[PDB]
Image 1 (spheres, rainbow, N blue to C red):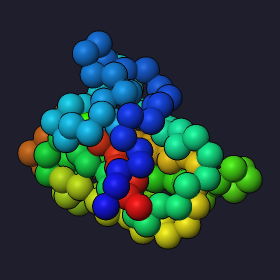
Image 2 (tube, helix red, strand yellow):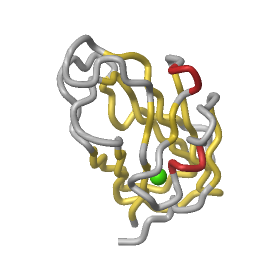
Image 3 (cartoon, rainbow, N blue to C red):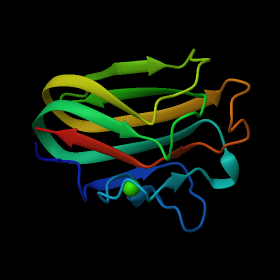
Amino acid sequence: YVNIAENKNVSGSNSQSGNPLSNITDGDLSSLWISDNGAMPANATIDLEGNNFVDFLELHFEKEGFRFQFKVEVEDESGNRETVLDMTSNTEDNKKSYNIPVKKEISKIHATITGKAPGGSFDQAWAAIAEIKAMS
Ligand SMILES: [Ca+2]
């Protein structure tokens, strides 16, 4: 597979110094975007520059065990925006990473961390994403 998201422009909400939005598409699963002052909601958008077939996305967090509530949406050149993964009511431990089928042409990826459920090992963690890949 080829990660067509790699080095694509990331826009979105404010970031902690040292942990910019650009860390979402740098290809490094260890480099993070972290929301500034741990603000929620926090959001990131990847511009794929026009419509590109995407088989699936991968959303990577720093490590397993957060309890973020989040959603992933895709959009085409049309303006048709659509939710592909909705974990906004999540209360359980999160996996380290999520595969998400798309199987169509898309032009943008939108990730939003809307909240966090109580408990687990990292209950004061700030909203943060290690990587989003778009495989074709
Ligand atoms: Ca990264």
